[PDB]
Length: 383
Image (cartoon, rainbow, N blue to C red):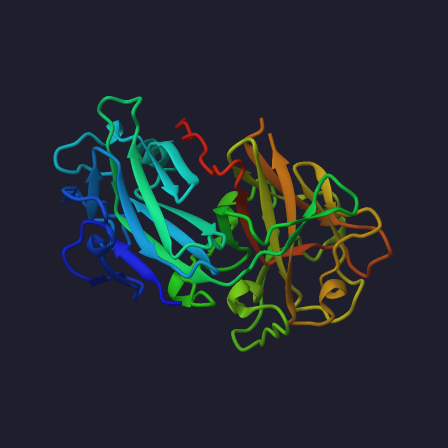
């Protein structure tokens, strides 16, 4: 399962700043006579000019056909650098993107989205379920509600991946689960909690995911205390696929800290802006690398003010895991419908008389589940 990493509009292969090789999109583009254009401004915040400084421009629909193994899951990454191309006004760009019959983006403004997020460029990442097709069709359609609309695209990646999704616990419900193995997903957030950014070249599974530090998403007054294991500390994955997350995610964590009393007076809280009217999977990654005994660190987990792990079954990482240095994760599903936020909160539990009063999280991923063959949300509005 080799990657296909296309720099759209490029004239030759090139390597980016993180050792990833990109090839031009031309051989996979089925639509003739489309415009390729360089960006005429290079933002200093770009980590590389590859693939961002070259684009395709579409004023009518255009289709890519990329060979895939139809029994395999694939990550799809769309790369957008809103800039000036062949004299066009980037604010006029509104378009949809489909993967086969799945709508990914609709009425999408890369420029307004970048403005709202204070970003120079955007990556939109999806995990596409096995399709039973030998070809992935990626279709770009300029908005027919905007007379001046065009579509653009700077990079497209198709990355074969393992079946990393299985089951999620339904947050509103006592003991109910749902199946996610055949879901189509949008990656909303991917955090190395308590740890450094991890570039794609250091990701596990050859999946070149980027894992971001979590501090910008903390919204409680206290930031807790970060925990770090030695770089030589061994994560013993056992049955968990190493492609789930790289070891440096499990070797770092955010906890509440050494004063159990202050910990019980607070929730460690993260907050995320998402799109309303979707079910989301919250994948919480855990690894205890300090304590060695069950019922030492025992905590409640709340998602959108509902108990995800609590009451008489609070979280105990070593209770789940059986050992120091063994990683795990738990998926929780929440339907969101002011309907545009997910909150994650942790605080110690008093159930069972734990030796300490603390909580901990090592990593976090948030995924949107497709509804009605659509993943598209509105553009964020800048403030």
